[PDB]
Image (tube, coloured by chain):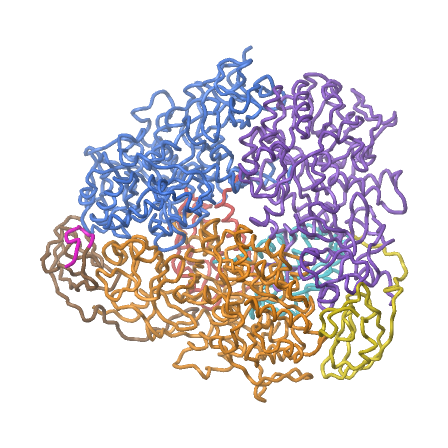
Chain colours: A yellow, B brown, C purple, D blue, E orange, F cyan, G red
Amino acid sequence: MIPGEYHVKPGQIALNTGRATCRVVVENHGDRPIQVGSHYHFAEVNPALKFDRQQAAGYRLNIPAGTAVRFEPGQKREVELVAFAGHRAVFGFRGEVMGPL
Amino acid sequence: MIPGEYHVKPGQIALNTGRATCRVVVENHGDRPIQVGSHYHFAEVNPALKFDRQQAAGYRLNIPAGTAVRFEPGQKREVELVAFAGHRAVFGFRGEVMGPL
Amino acid sequence: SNISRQAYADMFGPTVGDKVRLADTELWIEVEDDLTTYGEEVKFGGGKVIRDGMGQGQMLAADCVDLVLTNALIVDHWGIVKADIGVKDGRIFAIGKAGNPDIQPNVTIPIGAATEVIAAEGKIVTAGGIDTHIHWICPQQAEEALVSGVTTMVGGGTGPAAGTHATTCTPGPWYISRMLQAADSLPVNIGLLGKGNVSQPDALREQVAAGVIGLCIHEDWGATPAAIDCALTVADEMDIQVALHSDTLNESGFVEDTLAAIGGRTIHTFHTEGAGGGHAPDIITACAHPNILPSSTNPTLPYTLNTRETIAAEDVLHDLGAFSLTSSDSQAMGRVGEVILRTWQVAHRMKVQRGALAEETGDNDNFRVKRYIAKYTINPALTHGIAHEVGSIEVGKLADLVVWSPAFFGVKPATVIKGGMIAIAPMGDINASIPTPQPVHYRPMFGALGSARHHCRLTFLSQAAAANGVAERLNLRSAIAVVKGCRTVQKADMVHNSLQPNITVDAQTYEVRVDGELITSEPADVLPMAQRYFLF
Amino acid sequence: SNISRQAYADMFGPTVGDKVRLADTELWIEVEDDLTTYGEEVKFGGGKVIRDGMGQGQMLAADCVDLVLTNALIVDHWGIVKADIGVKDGRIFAIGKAGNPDIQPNVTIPIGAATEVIAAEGKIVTAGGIDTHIHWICPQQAEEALVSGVTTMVGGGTGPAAGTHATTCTPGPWYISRMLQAADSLPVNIGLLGKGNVSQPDALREQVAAGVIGLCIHEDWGATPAAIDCALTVADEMDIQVALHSDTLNESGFVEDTLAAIGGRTIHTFHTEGAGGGHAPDIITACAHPNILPSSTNPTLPYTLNTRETIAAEDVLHDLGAFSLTSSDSQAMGRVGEVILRTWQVAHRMKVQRGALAEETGDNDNFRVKRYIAKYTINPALTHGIAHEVGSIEVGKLADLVVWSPAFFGVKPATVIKGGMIAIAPMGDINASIPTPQPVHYRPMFGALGSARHHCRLTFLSQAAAANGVAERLNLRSAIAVVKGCRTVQKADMVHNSLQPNITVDAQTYEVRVDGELITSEPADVLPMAQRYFLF
Amino acid sequence: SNISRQAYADMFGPTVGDKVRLADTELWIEVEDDLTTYGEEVKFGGGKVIRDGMGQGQMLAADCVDLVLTNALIVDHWGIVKADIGVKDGRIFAIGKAGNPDIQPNVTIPIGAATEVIAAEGKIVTAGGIDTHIHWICPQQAEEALVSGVTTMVGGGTGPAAGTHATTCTPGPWYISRMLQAADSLPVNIGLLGKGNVSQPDALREQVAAGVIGLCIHEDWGATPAAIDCALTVADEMDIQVALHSDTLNESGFVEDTLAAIGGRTIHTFHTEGAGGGHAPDIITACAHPNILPSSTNPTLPYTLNTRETIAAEDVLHDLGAFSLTSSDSQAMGRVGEVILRTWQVAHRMKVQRGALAEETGDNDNFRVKRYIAKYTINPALTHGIAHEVGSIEVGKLADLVVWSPAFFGVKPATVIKGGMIAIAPMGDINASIPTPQPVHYRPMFGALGSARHHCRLTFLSQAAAANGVAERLNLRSAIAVVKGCRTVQKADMVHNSLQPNITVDAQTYEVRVDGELITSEPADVLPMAQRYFLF
Amino acid sequence: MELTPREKDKLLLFTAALVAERRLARGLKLNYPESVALISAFIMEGARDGKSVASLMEEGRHVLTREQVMEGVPEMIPDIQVEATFPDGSKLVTVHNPII
Amino acid sequence: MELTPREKDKLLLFTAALVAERRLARGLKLNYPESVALISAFIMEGARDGKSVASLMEEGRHVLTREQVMEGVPEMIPDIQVEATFPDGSKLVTVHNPII
């Protein structure tokens, strides 16, 4: 007996199903580490991260909401992105779009 | 080490410098003791104190501010007075002047 | 991508299919529905979802909620579901999927610059309780009740005086006006009951016109057929409720005479079980009538070793839905901070003894949980005509919410929200670098302060008092709500508690029977929500 | 039928002839009169008298009292009688026989649907005390005083500052206005005293116009003949009282010079005994003058082992009625919660040492009790011109009442009523099924809350401040009362304390003599109302 | 006559030349000037100077101060001098020589019948502290802060909610209005910060129009270049301040990108050291910029054994004046009651380790004391545009003063004055004959009560909110002050803390260097103002 | 003494712990609030003694064991935090899984 | 019990002293608040016992010595005052220079 204990049924959850995704190799060319969040507009991340910014347009990390991916200085890795939805209007970040698309 | 301790430089302080003073012999002719404060108009003290009230006009005790002089019944002593300043207007006390001088 | 269910539950709280134990009881709930879109859950914190251009939009204040409770496990009379709760203007705006419509799908609760966040992932959220059996013996009672999760208190009194010690009555215009003014200082919604014991109508009309939302007929002031009939007549014309504590001495007649005086008119019976008052000893038979809205108090809930026949029956009649409300009877045979706590103790004991209810579906206690929670939330609200303002988590209603950690459900709240602002909550060392260091104890928050309090609480008035401008005359500072629909409610309207059983009592042996079958239960030696949580 | 006197006393409290011991003192009171009609006493509870059609009538609110204190044993300057007390509109309506005129005889206090009940059978009821020697050093003093049974506090201060620590003065218009605003937050009646030490009239008039009901002349600000004369001149034209704490140093003259400056004008002398201030050491001679209204403080009451000639004399001068008031001199040589307590300790010690007073009739201490209770109730009220509002249990007066159980008389009150509502009272466990379980301690009630408080308390203003619209300008929320008759009161007006003895003091030996006879008393080693009641 | 310096110091406090140790630290101050006229010092008490016709004049209220603090040792950014302080209308009237012009010379602060007295001889008097990094997690924080000597609190929050736990933001119009109303109940000056994390200008303008005096940009809501630029644009047009807690994850760029987004515009950087937030790990380089007004929090002040490179550097950068403000970051990585206390601990540690500052003159720590006191008084005031109302002891400013006994300087205040009235102070037994008997602990005074409180506190509004009539609409009861000059302040304006050093950080080793020289300090094992003063 | 609100608040903790301490002495299995009070006060006295944060973070885990508290109690307390005045000012002590 | 505010207030002092008492037992040199609490409670119990003001004014000076408190503490306490109910009512006990 454990007060307020959970009895989670076993299995897995598929996230962001039914959405366009794409993989991208990203290399951190900076001297300081960089961490990107799940819903950040990938095409507007820290300029020190070198990758095909054009392909990542309107995409975000395909990871559980609230988590993040870290890139140590000089690190290189392939990440998977998932397309934004809703109105697909980007406002904020580095201010590169500030409108739909 | 003593929290909040003072380090008073040695020496003395001269009080009420540059002001007219006069000494007066005062005898307490009362049965009960009398205590006079530093800024009380001497000429208007307890009538039981016998002295030249005329000379003490517009004068107060030349003692550190806040202190006092006690006169036991039948006591006789010489005190030093210092002249009032500011506008030299006396209001209150026994109500003998109630105006300038 | 993909995430396992366990990792998912630890991150966003449990989802459809997962079961959660309520405190240390044997009751288990199962998430029936989850309104989220997997992978699009809003979460707050460094590098999380609720940030500019991401989970937070660009909309002006008018187009987004003021407060959002993320990933909440709702337990209400209508369902046990997982969802985000939106609060706007101090009222429940929506129950759905919060976020930014610019990048997220299915967003029904928009989050913008003006949105505050309360993280409810892993917590259970419920409506604020409603106690309709309060003796205003002391003002310290409102805090005790608020801390337990009760956000509305209906009752009567003037302080520690003989009349108030014995009955829930605020005698007359002067004291009524005085208590209405004093109410502005209390952090809970309030509605007063006047002295309904009189055989002259005008003497009652004056009280209703002064501000009371009901009339309490108590035997100490004389619960005679003449007084009962008089109070019900006025109730019928002014749309206010009548609360009865019948003649225990059988002085003017037996229970059947009382019921006859009532004449099939709507009425709320106090201590329908008998213990704390009522025609000795068959007042309990009232729960078989359509016009009777019955309640039991907490000092008898549940039948334990130190608390006999009617006491054992009460717990069962509650489990069957024959008794619709649970109240306290504060400081006059009941405990103000234990109404919610005791309701679940009974539910536990009944699960243990009687097993699953005939209405239960699935391997959970979901139905029994909905039937019991309705007893101290929605049903009290319907009985007193305030269900349009409070009573449940439904849109348009005052946001009186209570957040609970599963291990402390029903016992000690994590957050108590009044009309949109946190009013009280556990708080650690004030000088600490975080709010969690010991000693942690309940302390008043901004929702309980001066003008903010007034704006987040309601003083309920009768329609007449409202029309007469009582609020402007007394210069009441809090918001006002009017009661309505007290005469049209009946047993059948009591959510999940509309049973009208063929119940009988033996005048001699005091045994209670339902359809000839004997009703009874065994006294418990050890109960949950007890020694494991309290210091004293 | 017939009932024995013992059974009768246990049921309705003692009646004519019965004696009651006050706490653990040697003082005994005897019921002089009983206003009831035997067999028609009103009593509240299940199956009792106060019920619809029986002890409770059918009259509308306007024709019945709001609150009724049943079977009370009143102890007031005018008598020690048994009666029901009726309270209407926050004021004392009547002292007589409560009930329903439809079936009971001799009913003068009608009880109807709008009547609340406080059971006072077996209890002693008194007026609220009045302390006129308050240093407003901290606001926590009003609660301490309220708990002891003092409902009105007159004095001055601005908080913990040197000026206030030493004197009861609220210096000037700004601080006066500030203290008037702060007063709305306190559960006692309040009236301020300004700084009366000035030889320019306009400087005093401004203060009176700002709101003070008196001027305190204290030696620390300079109690010179010029200042004294100036304050008394303004007092005479504005109808406010002057409180003096004379020149101890004999700096401007001896006591005879002070008395000469006073010029036979009305004045209240603080610490007339000398200990806490006044011309060393014969200020005590003032009690022989017609225009002098003398008081003593509590730290010297009574002359005990750890507290000399004047201290011994004080207790006797009180017993003889030469000293008319007892006050505290709160946190500056006196105890705010011990004014009442110490008054009775002196009365006890004097009974023990001097026996019966020359005015005593019967085998009781009734007269000595009336003389001493007047010291902290009616006399302070007359001295400050507020006797039209408070001070005693008389019709038309503000209902500031204190209920006491005989075992705790003078020490710990059962109920403290302010303007018609209970303000503070002992209260047990808030979550208990009854209000009596431990821990029982004093807690604020509804009469002490926000707007209800304002309506049940009075802020006293000088006639000038009232005319100038000070209340509307400062936006004061509490009720207002104006003072009047401060210049026309004299020693002869002091109820049961008008003795002007030929008293002398020896400048050397400090011995006090009345008519040549030496006045003195012995220090007590053990007093009542002490270690038996207090935890610390 | 003549008096020795020691006797003089014991009587009136120290004079020119005398040194005083601050609590149990190694810091020593020396009286630089004394504004008195030897032999004419005002002193209060029996037979002292402040009495009618003597040290007290005959002038009407309009021509004399309301309160006078006699013989005070002032420690302010402009000097460490001895003088009398005059307070009139709740504002600092003069700093000079108090007394009666009729008999005393050089009187600049006239004392009359309307003058209250606070004896400050032997005490040190300072301005009230200003904390500009408050998370409104609970209302109990204002008392904790008031007791420590902080009289103004700027920050944001809505209570114990996730958003407030993490950031100093009051999200939107509704919560802003709610917090403004709740502020009337608190005994400190208050100004709110809204959520500045948005890329749509109108969403920010609404908040400023609702009442916030600033916008907090915190990384948890997304501190992106787009949001930063948007908040600074609106700040520039509405004359409000922006408080930044930069992107620690380097998600949108490094510190240089943040600085670039700022575009040389005025901004207050939170935790410029890095520990509690900011671009990991070179946010510290910001202190080299002219438009940056930097602050450090207290949990890192000073670098001790249990608290690394940046932490050691912070203490030095403070000693050099590169960091201008010290704040708390209440209950979210900082201690609300320790801002002042920790500022002096750093000063002590720096004296011990680095010796005298290059600016020091004489054998005292006067300059280091002025540089450090400015950090929590005047500089925070200039940074937020409220320096016209509070921040220092200068004429025309709100009289928010703190009185300290030298042994308890920086730790436990003798008196805390708010707008002219004592708000809180140590107070002994309420029932005692004096206010000094134990138990002595901090208790609210008259300046903290109802209407008096409102009159002695200020709610700061943005110019827009003020124009829109927000105060009249919300029915705010306290005095109002408007902010101005937040955009024109720069590093050079920070009193005694305007250093812009050529500072560098090593991305790998995290070492801080100033002009190539390595900056560092050693962790202390034992600090002053710690175990010697606190019970726990 | 000039006790501030925080010192007075810690007095509540000290007293709460006094209750727990006596109950443990009687041999009772402690409940949720008793356990927190007991371990919290332990740490406060450790700081008073001058022990370091690091030492206490370890010692705090050996005050009570799983067999000395009621069932479920160990899991209701994933950590215990308390601040006290050490010789070098106030510090935050966090004890993870104090009961094992 | 009907505890008034003053009785409840003295309970704060009693508890404060309980803390001091235990620390002294451990052999710690007491600080400012601990010293005041300890000597103050001592006097309160003296009055409860019925000792006279005079006796306590003397006994109060022998509770703690200079070697039992922290440096500077003796000078931070020029006197200690406390009131308690003696057999003959409340009295004020003042102990001058309690620590020597």
Q: Nearer the viewer, residue C374 or C56?
A: C56
Q: Nearer the viewer, residue F55 or E23?
A: E23
Q: Nearer the viewer, residue E355 or D221?
A: D221
Query: Which residue occupies 25% across, 46% down?
Result: D246
Q: Which of the 4 image quarters holds residue F11?
A: bottom right
Q: Residue furthest bottom?
A: E516
Query: Does residue C172 show up magenta in the picture?
Result: no
Q: Position of residue G73 (x, y in %)?
A: 45, 65
Query: Does residue B95 show up magenta in the picture?
Result: yes
Q: Position of residue C114 (x, y in %)?
A: 66, 59
Q: Which of the 4 image quarters holds residue E191?
A: bottom right
- Give the overall secondary structure of the magenta segment: loop
Q: Is C59 situated left or right of E378 in this image?
A: right
Q: Quadrant of the C terminus of chain F?
A: bottom right
Q: Position of residue E162 (x, y in %)?
A: 68, 60
Q: Nearer the viewer, residue C193 or A83?
A: A83
Q: Position of residue A61 (x, y in %)?
A: 81, 71
Tell me which segment is drawn in magenta.
Answer: B91-101
**Image position of D82 with respect to C293: above or below:** above
Q: Is C461 situated left or right of D342 in this image?
A: right
Q: Residue furthest top?
A: D1
Q: Is C66 situated left or right of E18 in this image?
A: right
**Image position of D193 with respect to A42: above or below:** above
